[PDB]
Image (spheres, coloured by chain):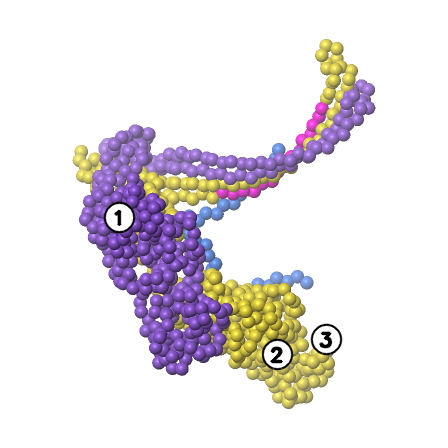
Chain colours: A yellow, B purple, C blue
């Protein structure tokens, strides 16, 4: 049962090994401590363990061995959750894609103030005068050409320096998924149509008894192929020549030549073909003559689309962290800028919520982001939870719209009147 | 809730921050203003905001900061729609394709006057004497060889200059789609027919008990293939030669040669094949002998076609805008001519109605057309709506016609009499 | 000469056939697309253990 770093600090009142009246500190959790020992322990500082052993701070190489000292047994006795307080989805007023996206990007309470605050906790640098932990006095929120948030340059002041830098938040290339029945596409319209091909046929059934269906099967297949090959060839030739020459016609210059040829080659390539292959088969239980018509065509298609509520959010932040100026531990301080991943949408290795959980459990997997735990030393990591919740929660609002694409193949089958036949 | 530029101008009577008695102006909408600040604000002019802040006109770089001033809080309190007044479809007298298209192109009330007026609002240049905002005194409406609208050259006068230019409106390459049951194709006629192939067969079932069906499956496949390849070859050869020569027949000129060959190539290509593959299978539960005949043929097909109401309209205008001479803002004034897209039919990025909506919401997406909002400064954008409606509304009239195409494959299956068989 | 080689092709081949016993006009739409998919997964009890010392 892994112990979270939050409460892990020293219990001042406690004695430890001599009888704390709490649940024992053990070896299993003790080994798990090594990566954040600096948070908990002073260089020389010593801490105990229930099996009659002790831990030492960063000053020493120390293995887990015998000693006497206090520590937290208290926290392990009653662990606390660590969870996000509320997952609830946000409801924003509905509209069209332009406006809905804007409202989301515009929202001070729902987007900006919380995103900025989260940024503040996470390491982002500050700019100029301040009002609270988020968006400063001079700071402002305007739109980038891309639709992202941006501010004016003139005032400057990042980290209290005259440089031009400003924080920006990207709008995502939105992607959505919808579990419910709540959305729909309307009737199609063909802007333009060209007719590629037609095929017609019929079944003639004069006789009374034998009645059977007819099958027309088509295939329209077009394909492209691409390949490249590289060949290496080596030629070895040894030759000898004599000048005796044979009187009739040996040849004055008589040469014999042997050539050995070796060549090898490797290649790769591939092709893709698309086929439109319709099959029509009328059962036609009637004594008749039945025309059938099968059509292939190309067209421009457009559909109006009914409003859909859900949207997924992809966020990566700006590169301000390098300016950040906070106690790092995991990373060295470096000038060159690095964009930090915020992924809200579910990508397991990328997503922030998981990383938050992972930091609590402690897992040594591969990582490329600044960790969550250093906030505990710096800010305490309390009462922040709602702020994180603001960023993490799903947001939805109905956006009505269009469905359109490049011109596509389409097809059709028409059936005629089964004309009465007689013998 | 984005605020439209229409009403956005200053409220003269209002004080602003000191207590307007209206709903507050806020930062979110304020940032959205930057692209049309020039319309609303004078260079030095100042405007307020509810969170104790102020905005400044184009003279300044100004960020959103503290100040005191009036603005519109009034409009935001009660927003107005911005919509097209009526979507209703136009009914034009029915006919054939030649006449129906003509009537549409001919209609003064429904086509010309409104299209010209819309053009006038949008930036199109004027020619000679005028009568109202649309089609001038000298101006006229005649037909181009293409079927487009055109006028005579002699009089001239575009922008009050002697040049030859005249406005023209294109007839679209019509494309239509039809949701309803309301249309049909009649009986087919074969103008010409050539018989490609025939295959015949039968099932003989003398014995009383075993009765089973027969399946004939065919495939006629023809295909074409095209490809091109490019190969690059590099040859490196080093050679040495000696003149010692070997007495018997070394060769006076003794050479040894080594050649290294390297070659590589890439290619692309593709092929398409069409197959006509019919399958016929009579169940034939009878003790009999049953002939079956399967035919492949080629033919010219023609169908009369029942009237269809709907038509979609594709419009792009003339290139007159460059002559236009109005306050641009978004575009610089340039002499070279550019054709401006009017798309009535639904193509999302192209269509005018969407662009009208987009201009109202404010979206920074990529754009290649003159924007809708400058009309507000120039004309006020009032009472225009019906005119826009005239252009935008769907129009329909039944056009009867023909369905024809190039010669096509067709096929047929005939079944014989199941002749009574006996053991 | 001697040679070896091979190729792999993947095909997505859907077939749709409405029975449609009605006197009508019936539109059908078939779509191909590419996407990123993710599923939450319910707890599973068993695990197999591979050990080499």
Mark 2 or mark 3, which is nearer the start of the sequence? 3
Q: Residue sitting at 41 percent across and 41 percent down?
A: A221
Residue drawn 40% across the image and 55% down it:
B369
Label 2 resides on the chain identified as A
Front residue of this view, candidates B218 and A337 = A337
- Residue A30: percent from the left, percent from the top? 65, 76
Q: For residue A377, which numbered disc appears in the image?
A: 2
Residue at the far bottom: name it. A13
Foreground disc of the pair 1, 3: 1
Q: Position of residue B408 (x, y in %)?
A: 32, 35
Quadrant housing residue B35: bottom left
What crowding class fits label 2: few (fewer than 14 Cα within 10 Å), some (14-19), or many (20 or more)? some
Quick check: C46 above or below B233? below
Asked which quadrant contains residue A40, the reply is: bottom right
Q: Same chain for marks 2 and 1?
A: no
Q: CA distance from mark 3 to mark 2?
A: 25 Å
The quarter of the rendered structure image containing the N terminus of chain A is bottom right
Circles 3 and 2, Cβ within 8 Å, touching? The answer is no
In the displayed structure, does residue B371 sit left or right of residue B290? right
Residue bearing mark 1:
B138
User: Is A334 displayed left or right of A61 in the figure?
Assistant: left
Circle 2: element type: helix
Compared to residue B189, the image places residue A302 above or below, namely below
Q: Chain of mark 3?
A: A
| Magenta range | A257-271
Report the residue at 46% width, 63% height from top.
A147
User: Which residue occupies the foreground of this view, A100 or A175?
Assistant: A100
- What residue occupies the far top of the structure in this picture? A248
User: In terms of secondary structure, what is the magenta stretch mainly?
Assistant: strand
Determine which residue is flagged by label 3: A63
For residue A372, the mark is none
At 72% from the left and 75% from the top, the residue drawn is: A63
């Amino acid at each position: 049962e892994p112990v979270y770093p939050d409460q892990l600090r020293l219990f001042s009142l406690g004695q430890g090994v001599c009888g704390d009246k709490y649940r024992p500190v053990n070896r299993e959790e003790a080994q798990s401590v090594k990566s954040n020992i600096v948070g908990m322990m002073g260089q020389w500082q010593i801490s105990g363990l229930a099996n009659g052993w002790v831990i030492m701070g960063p000053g020493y190489n120390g293995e887990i061995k015998p000693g006497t000292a206090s520590n937290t047994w208290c926290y392990p006795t009653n662990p606390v959750t660590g969870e996000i307080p509320t997952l609830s989805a946000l409801d924003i007023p509905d509209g069209d894609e332009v406006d809905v996206q804007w409202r989301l990007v515009h929202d001070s309470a729902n987007f900006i103030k919380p995103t900025s605050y989260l940024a503040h906790y996470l390491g982002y640098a500050w700019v100029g005068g301040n009002h609270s932990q988020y968006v400063g006095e001079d700071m402002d929120v305007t739109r980038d050409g891309d639709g992202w948030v941006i501010r004016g340059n003139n005032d400057g002041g990042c980290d209290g320096y005259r440089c031009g830098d400003k924080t920006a938040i990207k709008v995502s290339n939105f992607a959505y998924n919808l579990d419910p029945d709540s959305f729909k596409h309307g009737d199609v319209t063909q802007s333009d149509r060209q007719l590629v091909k037609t095929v017609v046929g019929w079944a003639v059934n004069d006789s009374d008894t034998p009645q059977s269906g007819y099958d027309v099967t088509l295939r329209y297949d077009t394909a492209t192929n691409w390949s490249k090959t590289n060949t290496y060839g080596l030629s070895e030739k040894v030759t000898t020549k004599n000048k005796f020459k044979w009187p009739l016609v040996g040849e004055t210059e008589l040469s014999i030549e042997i050539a050995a040829n070796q060549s090898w080659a490797s290649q790769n390539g591939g092709s893709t073909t698309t086929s439109l292959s319709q099959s029509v088969r009328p059962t036609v239980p009637a004594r008749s003559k039945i025309p059938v018509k099968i059509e292939l065509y190309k067209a421009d298609i457009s559909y109006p689309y009914e409003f859909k509520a859900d949207v997924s959010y992809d966020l990566t932040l700006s590169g301000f962290l390098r300016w950040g100026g906070n106690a790092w531990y995991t990373h060295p301080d470096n000038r060159p800028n690095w964009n930090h991943t915020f992924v809200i949408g579910p990508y397991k290795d990328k997503a922030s919520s998981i990383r938050y959980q992972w930091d609590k459990r402690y897992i040594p997997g591969e990582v490329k982001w600044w960790d969550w735990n250093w906030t505990i030393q710096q800010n305490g990591l309390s009462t922040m939870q709602n702020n994180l919740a603001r960023v993490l929660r799903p947001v939805r609002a109905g956006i009505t719209g269009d469905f359109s694409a490049e011109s596509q193949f389409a097809g059709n089958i028409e059936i005629g009147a089964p004309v009465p036949l007689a013998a």
